[PDB]
Image: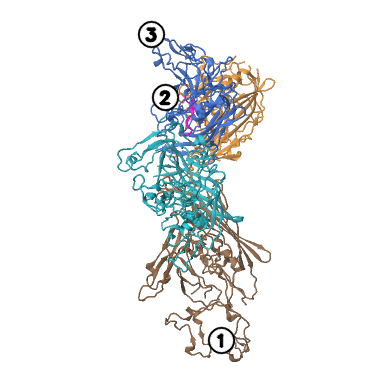
Chain colours: A orange, B blue, C cyan, D brown
Amino acid sequence: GVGISTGTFNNQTEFKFLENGWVEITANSSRLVHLNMPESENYRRVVVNNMDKTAVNGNMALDDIHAQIVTPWSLVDANAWGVWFNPGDWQLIVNTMSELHLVSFEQEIFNVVLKTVSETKVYNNDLTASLMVALDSNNTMPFTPAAMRSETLGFYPWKPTIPTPWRYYFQWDRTLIPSHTGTSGTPTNIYHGTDPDDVQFYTIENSVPVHLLRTGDEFATGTFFFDCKPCRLTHAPYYSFEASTQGPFKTPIAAGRADGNPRYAFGRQHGQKTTTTGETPERFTYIAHQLNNVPPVYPNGQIWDKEFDTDLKPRLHVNAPFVCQNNCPGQLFVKVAPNLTNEYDPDASANMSRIVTYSDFWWKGKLVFKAKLRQQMSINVDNQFNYVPSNIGGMKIVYEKSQLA
Amino acid sequence: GVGISTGTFNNQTEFKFLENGWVEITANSSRLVHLNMPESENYRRVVVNNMDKTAVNGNMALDDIHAQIVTPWSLVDANAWGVWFNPGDWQLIVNTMSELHLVSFEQEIFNVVLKTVSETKVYNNDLTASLMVALDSNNTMPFTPAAMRSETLGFYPWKPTIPTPWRYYFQWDRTLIPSHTGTSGTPTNIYHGTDPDDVQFYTIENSVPVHLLRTGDEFATGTFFFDCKPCRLTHTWQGYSAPYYSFEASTQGPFKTPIAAGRADGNPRYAFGRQHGQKTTTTGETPERFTYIAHQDTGRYPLNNVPPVYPNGQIWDKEFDTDLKPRLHVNAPFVCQNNCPGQLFVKVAPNLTNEYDPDASANMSRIVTYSDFWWKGKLVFKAKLRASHTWNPIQQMSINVDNQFNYVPSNIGGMKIVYEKSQLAPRKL
Amino acid sequence: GVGISTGTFNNQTEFKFLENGWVEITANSSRLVHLNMPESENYRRVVVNNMDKTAVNGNMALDDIHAQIVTPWSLVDANAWGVWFNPGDWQLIVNTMSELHLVSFEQEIFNVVLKTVSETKVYNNDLTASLMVALDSNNTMPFTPAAMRSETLGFYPWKPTIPTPWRYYFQWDRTLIPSHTGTSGTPTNIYHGTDPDDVQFYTIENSVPVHLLRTGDEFATGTFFFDCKPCRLTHTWQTNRALGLPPFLNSLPQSEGATNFGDIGVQQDKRRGVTQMGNTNYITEATIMRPAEVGYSAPYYSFEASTQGPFKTPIAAGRADGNPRYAFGRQHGQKTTTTGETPERFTYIAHQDTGRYPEGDWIQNINFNLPVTNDNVLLPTDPIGGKTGINYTNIFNTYGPLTALNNVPPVYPNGQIWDKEFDTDLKPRLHVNAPFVCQNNCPGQLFVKVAPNLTNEYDPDASANMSRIVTYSDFWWKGKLVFKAKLRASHTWNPIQQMSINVDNQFNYVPSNIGGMKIVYEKSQLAPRKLY
Amino acid sequence: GVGISTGTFNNQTEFKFLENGWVEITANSSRLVHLNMPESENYRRVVVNNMDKTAVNGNMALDDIHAQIVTPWSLVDANAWGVWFNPGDWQLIVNTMSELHLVSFEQEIFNVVLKTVSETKVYNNDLTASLMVALDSNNTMPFTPAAMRSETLGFYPWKPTIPTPWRYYFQWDRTLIPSHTGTSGTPTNIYHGTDPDDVQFYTIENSVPVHLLRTGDEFATGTFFFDCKPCRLTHTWQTNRALGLPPFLNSLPQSEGATNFGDIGVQQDKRRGVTQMGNTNYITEATIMRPAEVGYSAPYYSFEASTQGPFKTPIAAGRADGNPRYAFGRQHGQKTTTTGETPERFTYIAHQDTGRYPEGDWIQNINFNLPVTNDNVLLPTDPIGGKTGINYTNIFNTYGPLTALNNVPPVYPNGQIWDKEFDTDLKPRLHVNAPFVCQNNCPGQLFVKVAPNLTNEYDPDASANMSRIVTYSDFWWKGKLVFKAKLRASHTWNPIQQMSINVDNQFNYVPSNIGGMKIVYEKSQLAPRKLY
């Protein structure tokens, strides 16, 4: 019933030394996930357009036009290195391993809590409510990794996290004619529409089976198994763009030398010193010491990515060190179910009235690696106070290098 | 479920006699433990610096400068004699036993209650919330014995108790040069910092498995068996010397030299609160104190193991990790040779409001929550009955007209637990 | 879980019949027990002293000095007849059965409910809180029968009852030298304190395992089995004068009438017989040697003082003096619709005879000059020590090897069923408060307590008393007391006395028109029995 | 647990057809029963005494004098036809079936919901409270059928219903000497009290096991099996005059018409046959012997007195006198939208005849001079005792050995199904209140009561009533009542009378605009039966 705990928290990293110099690294991660109800229950097709900001000449790069489907579901995405390791185990990993294999992965949701709010405020339990959960075992919905927009789960184990609200790109048509400063006119810059052949409207309910979870039950994924090739730990015009119906896009660069090497911007969930004020994210440029695979990036580096469905297939992915050879883990989508009031009628155009409900549920992840034992990464006077908390409770995770030897 | 209890309260002390003059002494103990949520979840690195008191010349002994990690957890510690034995059982043990061993220790948390508070206050059961419990099985965390700070559980089975909030020493660099009162100059007094090489930052989440306990399920520690040497409940009437009141110093600051003997210099002086011996209905913040003047006469005017001190003294302690280990520990009679029983850490889980978002730098908004959970443990000893070698009788503890009323309550609920000596019998050296 | 009932209510009485005349009387009793939380969680050593009432000269008997350890626990005690039998069953037992054994006993608490109070008032279920239950099976703790204080459970299955807050005598030392009205000064009336070696501080927590019960669990004791001697539901009418062969009447009467008596045909000094007064020729029914003595005189209303203070001497058999007096409240027999604090009272005048009549006794000189002179005889009229109100019977004591007595009768509904034997080396021959006495061990006392339900502001290092959520519990109690009894036989031509409803006591056994019930005392030893 | 349902609502009637022309009618019934807590938890003894109304002369029949023991418990009674059947099912019974037996019966309470009210009004649940449920399987309690007060469960499946508060008769003595308007003084009219040898105070706690039901458990009464005689759904038209062989007719009619009668040829003083009136040669249809007497004349609107005051003499079969008059409320047939205190009423005019016509009766002298003079005949126009309004038929009784009766017909929807046979040594041949009579045991009555939900201010020693949390409970009752019925076969050429819907009675069997519903009365015995 309600009073039985359904799981156990686990955030230890286990290093099981095997025969012939191999080692199995089991990274357990566990977070307390907070989830508020959706803003609206209906899917919305919204087109953003910053024409007033980019109709001016000489800022072709500042283009934001994109059509996306706002989906009420929220995405639980642990695809980032910071979710699984603190600086101690990554220090051990970079210092003592040589190659690294991505082995297996599982998740589970446990100890679901659902609460309601009413007027001053009072918070009450709703034992009858439910949390809608869906796992995309067959990848019906599009693959949307949250590490790109920096919206994965928080890297700190002892603080809660929120899942990112889920959305995907609609397919549209756009043309923009570039120009330099002092150009003698306004180039063409319009939003055509959507090609009907490219219209695709995915929905979680039609696609994936949804498990309704009350306060006393669980959802658990199967142990999804990888077969990716290993990544070694031992170790192109500039000012260029291209364009299509998507609009302009900066060209890809295979390897490094606010340009060249990749720059990561991030917030307080994702390694920034938590207690600093302001909305400004803290940033780093990953100047690595260096086909050759891209290097991992503690903690905003994405771990895995999907192979493309195109006839062509690139030699390497710019954004992740590993790539799904044939299949990826299923994306986990969550949503607090509609808690309706008695005044609901569906034949009124007004949006439905709902009881203000929110959910707290614990997530546990397990991620297994296999690695072969081979500078020395170490603490020093300069970097010392980055790896311990402040007086008033702040903490940061400075980025670190994945290839030293 | 919610409506079914999970364990039984027990404070019985059981004497089971065995062959060859040995006695098994099973000391059960049970308490009701009140746990508030942490003041803040974030791990804090706090430095305290009493330079105002220490800078005055002659105040070297008042050095209270240190650095500590303030954990968002609390420790349930039962490493004190008073938790297990009432005065009558201690009288029986001291008066009839010559030697004493340890056998085992287990624990459990049962009947979790988890309540919330709303504004005039009104109290509501939140059946869904969880109590985090983590037992450091492998002794990964620093061992922080609670008896030295009088932080152990209460010694009265009827009064509820509280767990100590947990905190451990971070490393700090410090130096102080002494100066007597009347010295005109100001000595060196500086907090140097902390060595990078010696930094250690542990968290409960990454170090130990953490069980969640809703309001109808248990946690049970397996019976951890000791291997300690015998403790003698007799004193030799028939020693060593040391520098009196000499304060040595190191990277962390000054520290007094421990002495393996005593007269009142050298003898340990305890200070404790109302949970742990002081009369419960006396007002004021001052602690009750005594000095344990042992019978063994190991000291000399200006070796054998330390006495047991009832009710405030320790039972066991962890052996040092150094290659060369000391002859004895000044603070407990027994010492675990490879591992001590694991430390039990408890915490009320976060209970967030709808307003929460982590991109704000401020502390999280929460629903006020507190936990009442029953705790039970059993501590297994093994003792040998004495034999009357001498013609005369030995000294024995006894109620008498002076100490009579210490052992029974007052006209109101006042109770106190006075210390008794623990090696009354003499032994031939 | 929470919503499943965990037991049944049963207040039936079953009379199962066995071969050879025996009957098994299984008496089920069930109640709804209401328990408020303790006034304070701590143990208190309270000392009571009514020095002002006792300092007045002549009030030796009004002493109430004692020292009691007040305890947060409450005791669920069912040791009284009214808890088990209603008046109709008692009619059946006393009228039909002769002997009455005690076979077994068991208890169980079930369907625990537990609520909280908060301010107007709102009552909320507090499911996760606990009721704290203990059963002292080994009888390590002091025995405390609730029957003596009118503190047992209620005698109505349809009224909720309450448990008694438990308390036991701590040791004390006291001296109270007597006085009469208008004595020369103030006698010594001081409270010494407590001697150290008799101190005994008991607590539930250290002594017995305590079970924690939530809204959805039970506690049941085992079936205790007694070994008590039989109690007799008959009574003996024969004093010494009624034993043996009566004298041969040589001259029987020739007509009916109270005035026409029979006559013994031989002069008193010429009669034949056997007598113990060897220096006398007279043989009379007052002087003929009987086989033994039935009953015994005792110094009635004598007070003796051990170290704890004065107390009355118990008298084994009554006539007045000796006969017990029961005072009881509205749970236990007083009319429930009455106002005021005055208890309803009765004196149980037992039918059993074998008492003494102190105004009829006398002592005379050994020489035995039968028309006795004043100087050779001592009467109840004669003062002892010059006090006009005291005579020799107030100090006399005929207890000896020749004395024979009966056990005290049962007293429905307020009396006590069983009792524990003293732990002394030499034990008493009877108990004045119960017919059955456990020889080795008695039913274990059952203790109950509402567990601490703390508020967020708890701080055990502070000296102030703890703040608790106001909690209270209602739990159903059920018990099963099994008797074994023999049926009587019509030994004699005449009928015997039986209990019966008549026009006088009719309305004592049915409720009034506003719900007022009462239970009135019934005699227990109606039928006569041959002593010799 | 709390959230798992524990039964299924069912109100189907299933007609299973066996071989040899029998039908097993499985009557299921289900009702939501609402129950408030008792008004007062004590058993009360209340005397009703309307001396004001019966002291007016001539109001003797308005004697409402009685003592009863009002109890906290409430009774669930389903002993009425309307609870089990609807008009369509009743039609299929009475139009098709000849005999009806009673086979089985079982009950079950399920899905107990308990709620508490706190002052605006907010209705909170109380998952820990309990509902007491008792079953008198042994029939130890006083039997109390609720049909004779119209307090059975309601007859509509969708409406919720309430159980009757329970009460039973205590003993009393009364005398009421009758009088008429214009009498010279006040007759004796006094409540004598109660006699001790007849006192009987039953309590549910002491006499049956009582189960506690929390929200999540059931109580299932086992299947009770009847042994009652067949109730017949046919009626007997044959009076004494219709028995036997008719006379031979010589002059049969030759034309059709209202006045075209036949004639018996022989003179009345020359007919052949057998007659009882031996001194009379004349043979005729009022004279010819018949095998036995059908029906009996009884003294109508006669009253007799016993220790408990006056009462009416019942009559087995009515023609007015004897015909039962049913008064009933909105649960039990009256139009549910009606307002005000007035029961809907019907008088059940049975089809069966077997009655008497008092204005047609007469007695004449044994000589029997045929054109009887005035002084040789006692007509119903003749006074008895000089009273012009009271004739000989008012005091007449001709029950005898030759008297044949039919059992009382069923009455739909308010008629009682079964009744308990008297515990007397000599038992009545028929009961007038229900067709079936249980020879040894009827089904155990099912008593219900909300448990005491106390507050923290309770002490038993207070004279005032205990303070309770205002509680009420809703629980689902289910019942099955299995019959066994024989299908009729058409013996006659002609068609029989049948129940049928028509234009006049159309809107009695369907609801109104505002949801009102009514259940009108239906005739039970329709098809004629061959008596002889």
- Where does residue A404 sit, x and y in percent of width and height? 60, 16
Amino acid identity at mark 2? Pro
Residue D466 seen: no
Please tell me whether residue D158 is drawn above or below residue C227 in the rendered image. below
Magenta-span inclusion, residue D182: no
Please tell me whether residue B167 is drawn above or below residue D296 in the rendered image. above
Secondary structure of residue under mark 3:
loop
Q: Residue furthest top?
A: B184
Secondary structure of residue under mark 2:
loop
Residue matched to label 1? D259
Residue matched to label 2? B287
Q: How crowded is mark 3: few (under 14 residues within 10 Å), some or many (20 or more)?
A: few
- Label 3 near label 2: C-beta < 8 Å? no
- Where does residue A227 sit, x and y in percent of width and height? 67, 27
Residue matched to label 3? B183
Amino acid identity at mark 3? Thr
- Circle number at residue B124: none
Q: Say which of C64 and B368 sits in front.
A: C64
| CA distance for labels 2 and 1 | 128 Å
Quarter occupied by the C terminus of chain B: top right
Quarter occupied by the N terminus of chain B: top right
- Where does residue C483 sit, x and y in percent of width and height? 55, 51
On the image, which quarter does residue D261 sit in?
bottom right
| CA distance for labels 3 and 1 | 157 Å
Query: What secondary structure predominates along the stretch shown in magenta?
Result: loop
Left or right, residue C50 beside residue D345: left
Q: Are marks 2 and 1 on the same chain?
A: no
